[PDB]
Length: 137
Ligand SMILES: CC1(C)CCC(CN2CCN(c3ccc(C(=O)NS(=O)(=O)c4ccc(NCC5CCOCC5)c([N+](=O)[O-])c4)c(Oc4cc5ccnc-5n(COP(=O)(O)O)c4)c3)CC2)=C(c2ccc(Cl)cc2)C1
Image (cartoon, rainbow, N blue to C red; front, side, top):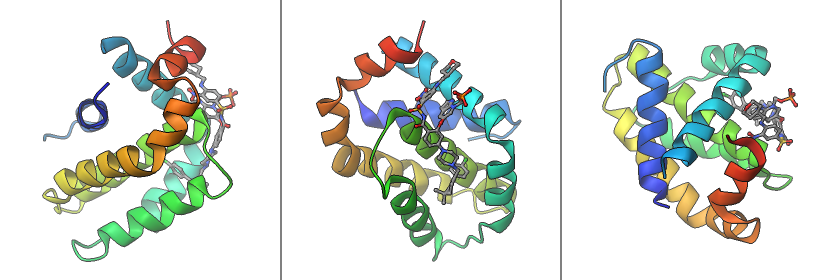
């Protein structure tokens, strides 16, 4: 599994499902899990999208701050879905505010975070195959 491909497909999904412009079972499962997360956590989304103040200079710090807090008490599959959903929220708020070049930077930051911070937990917990076994078709 390629974390970059996982990230790229997810962001492309988040943007196109909202009218913006920019192995398959893993992508499909993540789409379903993330759509479920956004239906169940609507109030957390509205608060994040409204409170999140972004500029090309502070975007990485904003991303890093939220993601550290999300994973502070440990990693679980639910928290990883929330990480992709948070990444999607940043991408949508970046396009909304005409800072669209930030989308490519967010994809890079999400890819590095998966490869350097989440990779250990993912493999120790069965890999993406285990996520598909728990929540997929
Ligand atoms: C950190 C901040 C600064 C502050 C707080 C926030 C908000 N905050 C909201 C709560 N949240 C967590 C954390 C952990 C779990 C958990 O251990 N899930 S889990 O591992 O037990 C688990 C069960 C089910 C599923 N899939 C089930 C579906 C069913 C339909 O088919 C597809 C699979 C998963 N999973 O990984 O897929 C996995 C969790 O529970 C879920 C996860 C889900 C993820 C998806 N749905 C799911 N449901 C909803 O399920 P329930 O009905 O059981 O409530 C509940 C929610 C953390 C983040 C911040 C913020 C972040 C992002 C944005 Cl965009 C905006 C703000 C930022």
